[PDB]
Image (tube, rainbow, N blue to C red):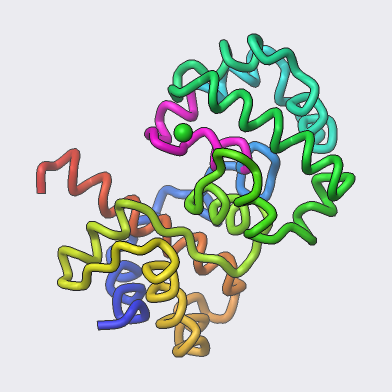
Amino acid sequence: LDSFEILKALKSLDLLKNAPAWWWPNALKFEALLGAVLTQNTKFEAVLKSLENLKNAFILENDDEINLKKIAYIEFSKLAECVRPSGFYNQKAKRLIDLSGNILKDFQSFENFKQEVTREWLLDQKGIGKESADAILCYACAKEVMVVDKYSYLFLKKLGIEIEDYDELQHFFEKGVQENLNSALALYENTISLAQLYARFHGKIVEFSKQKLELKL
Ligand SMILES: [Cl-]
């Protein structure tokens, strides 16, 4: 049992038949960074409601450089009201405002941020945990990072491997792909990058786990 074996098994189930190319809706856009932050300690279905409030108030529109500045400079109580559905709305409003302001300060633009950001820079933004930092790196910045989470932990535990530490759980998932890189890329007929492969692999694990729960299994 390595992660390349798990990737092949999950691939064979066609779990992402109705999903977009990078699994996360609106991947590689500022909206993906916002959802990666808002999903912490909650369910993605609640995040979609917060994102809808942001679009309905015209805080989030079509130009991502403008979107970044709107969050950096928004009135706190206005943002907190919009993000109520995804919970912890005072902490999450402040975390978004501060993160957005620091992206402008250190990188000047969302475009440059996607090129130059590091995981440690994101972890130095107060309140951003490892799952959220890695989801930004993969699904917003197209970096070769695989996100892990409680679902991945429980999924591997059921198969008989318990890795409670986030970075070691991540390294287990990454290294099996790295050690078998030619084979892993051939699953997609060499049409996708390793970053997109990790985007989809984490998506498979989540889709498998959500169904296990709704179907009771
Ligand atoms: Cl939180």
User: Is 181 left, or right, of 63 in this rendering?
Assistant: left
User: Is 194 left, or right, of 170 in this rendering?
Assistant: right
Farthest residue, direction right: 108
Q: What residue sits 65% from the left and 10% below the top?
A: 78
Query: Is residue 100 within the magenta segment?
Result: no
Up-down: is 30 above or below 168? above
**Residue 138, image x and y in percent?**
59, 58
The majority secondary structure of the magenta stretch comes to helix
Foreground of the two, 3 or 80: 80
User: Is 198 left, or right, of 16 in this rendering?
Assistant: right
**Residue 91, image x and y in percent?**
54, 25
**Residue 12, image x and y in percent?**
30, 70
Q: What residue sits 18% from the left and 48% below the top?
A: 212
Determine which quarter of the picture holds residue 98: top right
Q: What residue sits 19% from the left and 64% below the top?
A: 157
> For the N terminus, which image quadrant?
bottom left
**Residue 216, image x and y in percent?**
10, 42
Up-down: is 40 above or below 217? above
Q: What residue sits 31% from the left and 51% below the top?
A: 150
Region in magenta: 33-49
Q: How many marks?
A: 0
Query: Is residue 46 within the magenta segment?
Result: yes
Foreground of the two, 197 or 165: 165
Up-down: is 153 above or below 140? below
